[PDB]
Image (cartoon, rainbow, N blue to C red; front, side, top):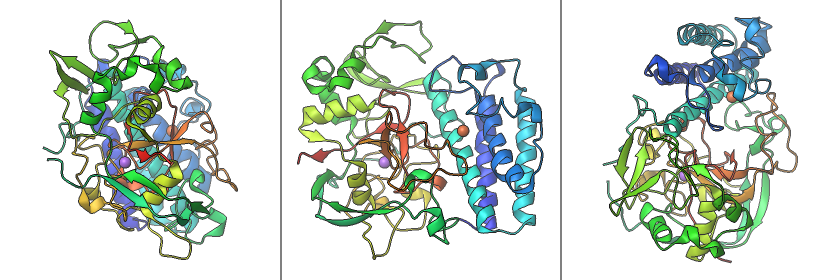
Length: 447
Ligand SMILES: [Fe+3]
Ligand code: NA
């Protein structure tokens, strides 16, 4: 993108996603059950609109907030999670929609009527992408609480078989390139070198040879681990995993049914019915297909499956090498397949929702033959989410700084995220306990 036409089309597409997410709910659904992983949908709309005012309109022009009384209430750093559920502190769906439409129009007016400097373009992209982060969170909120799929989604997926594009790819030892230049080091920091602070600054790594699966772990592969007692056999689980395994949760959360407190013995959204596995897909239970990727599993579940399988997770640097194969002084790519985004090459944009065969999208393949490095699921890596040496915070300095060390790095972009913000250098931190985000994994051979 980067051109005004692409920018403005992205702005309207994002606005329409947000509006479809809040407007297709009944009024009584706007107040969602509390869960530490969701937010109320009117609040996410107002918060993601406010970001534009803070970091584009007021930032560049000194423009006052549309409603200055809201500045601390729409702020995600100042507003405690639980307080976002107030029916009194926040406007109505109708008024928040009107607020959004006004700000989206100011955005388009400003894009058209002011110079497209690197500084402005950088902030336009950042704010639009931040709103798309909330398009993803709003989509998974529905899954967490058992609401219907969004009207734009096609959650039954690619109906679409599995093929002999499997096996490991071997990445030869060598010196590879990770990340993107620091903003101050690149005149293309608004365009070709755009990324978030955690992608920067770029560095070289001496990589030992390794072998990585060409395909995501499938339901059918994971099902064997589950059915042979994997969750009851703590030899496969790490110290953290065993603690997670012992936690007591409401296993019925999001199902429509009363609370059922218990320990987890299989992926949270799976349910065996008369010996056949099912998965909750928003407000429906669908049969679990063997060749679709296993998804919405914690880091610990992925980690224990690897131990059982005689495999390991990739580090995030092995992951990015296998996805993009960039070397210093050679031509760089941002996607496994090259540098031009085509949404048909990957499962993103809140469409198939991860129900695709793990060998699908051959045009999205990496230079080593790995399929669906981008899209389908965010992939767990072995690393704690940490700043690269030389890190500098973005103008919005909380993009990364609250999630270091406690979270894992995940890579690639999940099915509910938007393709317009994704890159192979992208890093999405997730707490390792979470079962509520669109996470999956592929494995590597032991060293
Ligand atoms: Fe936010
Ligand atoms: Na992926």
